[PDB]
Length: 114
Ligand SMILES: Cc1noc(C)c1-c1cc(S(=O)(=O)NC2CCCC2)c2cccnc2c1
Ligand SMILES: Cc1noc(C)c1-c1cc(S(=O)(=O)NC2CCCC2)c2cccnc2c1
Image (cartoon, rainbow, N blue to C red; front, side, top):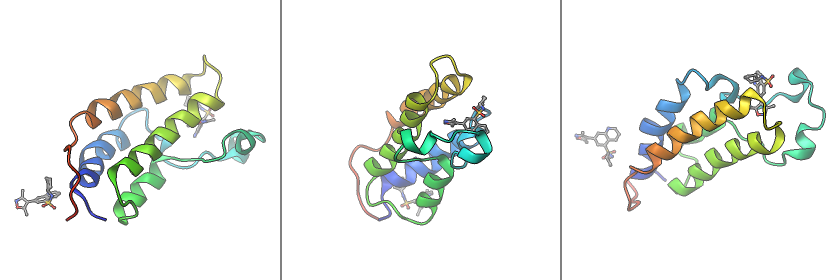
């Protein structure tokens, strides 16, 4: 579906996050071979990244905004679960997610199809 809320997530939320200076590690799926993490996919069962979310927005994959919000959430949660507490990537994820939440607080409240 195209909905008012999904449009907002695309044009306001994703727009802001995608261009952020800390976004780069999250713009494509985690490549476990490249990063040297043979257990990544053993620990993280549902990988997610902003490249995938952007494409889903662009291709009208989502039926409701809440679905897209859960993908954003999964991407951040994966990061917090996998990485060590002191890893810089955790700080970068937190920074992005703060913007995610700030923007989500201003999303249109009633979802309507277009
Ligand atoms: C401005 C304007 N003047 O005439 C038209 C037509 C627009 C308009 C309408 C929509 S929408 O109807 O698809 N979604 C609405 C629902 C919530 C707010 C946007 C946009 C959608 C995306 C970008 N520009 C949009 C601009
Ligand atoms: C693991 C992992 N789990 O979620 C994400 C996201 C990652 C992650 C981690 C690294 S890194 O640890 O090599 N560099 C850190 C240093 C500070 C920036 C990230 C990447 C390195 C390159 C590309 N993607 C990366 C993605």
